[PDB]
Amino acid sequence: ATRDEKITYLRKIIGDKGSDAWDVAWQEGVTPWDQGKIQPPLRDFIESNDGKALVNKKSDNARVLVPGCGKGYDAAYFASLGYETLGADLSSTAIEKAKEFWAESPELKSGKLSFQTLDFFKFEVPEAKYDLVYDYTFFCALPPDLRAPWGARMRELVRPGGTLITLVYPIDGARSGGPPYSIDVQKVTDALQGSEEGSAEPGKYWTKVLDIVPQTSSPDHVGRERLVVWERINK
Ligand SMILES: Nc1ncnc2c1ncn2[C@@H]1O[C@H](C[C@@H](N)CC[C@H](N)C(=O)O)[C@@H](O)[C@H]1O
Ligand SMILES: Cc1cc(C)c(S(=O)(=O)O)c(C)c1
Ligand SMILES: [Cl-]
Ligand SMILES: [Cl-]
């Protein structure tokens, strides 16, 4: 079937089954988002001077979370940098296929990399929280009414002074419907900064330290993508 057809179906079964539709999609092989590798802006950020700084300052027990990790390319990448890394996905099928795709990873073998079937909204945040979290094609997978809970979870998941990286894609403008929902930095901002009763005036919970157009985007991502680095505050 075509990509449009696979997306049309995906949106059907989400309409009928809700969040259970994802493991169905994985079981049936309707995974049109799967690229087989990380997106280049992630590696370029990490190898950039800002990224080297972030990695060099990592504590000896620094922990990474990649929610909605799918086949887990991003989690495998962060583990290969020496971070103890958990890739979390709602679909047990996705998590099994991530264990297959990464079966030869030295970090999987050692346990430094770990894949687990987990609901991002429900699992128990560890006491130490996470030093670094990476969100790619997860915020844009969620229905719009789940964006505020996503930001609330994000605020609990990242330790004070820790970092959240959002590869914001797809920035398609006013197109309606999803997945993949058309998003932008403002939508990520509003979700992450939440509200303070009276208003949502930013600088409450995060500092947006970096917001760039990546220089190396996949060709179908050019013009629809921004990379954003957030630091958690209110220590
Ligand atoms: N509440 C949830 N908790 C954890 N994972 C979820 C949740 N809802 C949806 N997902 C997963 O989010 C993934 C969205 C995928 N389209 C993208 C996967 C991955 N980020 C990639 O770049 O390949 C799916 O694998 C879902 O199983
Ligand atoms: C969650 C989600 C779903 C889909 C179908 C896609 S994609 O087809 O555009 O690649 C992406 C990027 C994310
Ligand atoms: Cl990769
Ligand atoms: Cl934007």
Image (cartoon, rainbow, N blue to C red):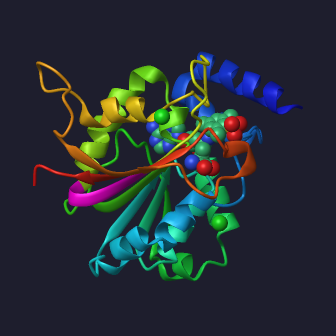
Q: Is residue 176 left or right of residue 163?
A: right
Asked if one can make out residue 90 in the rendered structure from this viewpoint, the answer is: no
- Depth check: 73 or 121 in front? 73
* Residue 36 image point, x, y percent: 72, 58
What segment is highlighted magenta in the picture?
Answer: 159-165
Residue lying at 34% horizontally and 68% vertically, measured from the top left: 63
Q: Position of residue 13 (x, y in %)?
A: 67, 22
Q: Which residue does the image show at 33% across and 31% down from the upper left?
A: 191
The residue lying furthest to the right in this view is 1
User: In the image, 55: left or right of 75?
Assistant: left
Q: Is residue 73 magenta?
A: no
Q: Quadrant of residue 203?
A: top left
Q: Quadrant of the N terminus?
A: top right
Main SS, magenta residues: strand
Task: Using the image, determine if residue 44 lies above or below residue 212.
Answer: below
The residue lying at 72 percent from left, 41 percent from top is 31
Is residue 41 in sight in this rendering? yes
| Image coordinates for residue 93, horizontal then vertical, percent | 64, 49
The verdict on residue 163 being magenta is: yes
Quarter residue 61 falls in: bottom left
* Quarter residue 181 falls in: top right
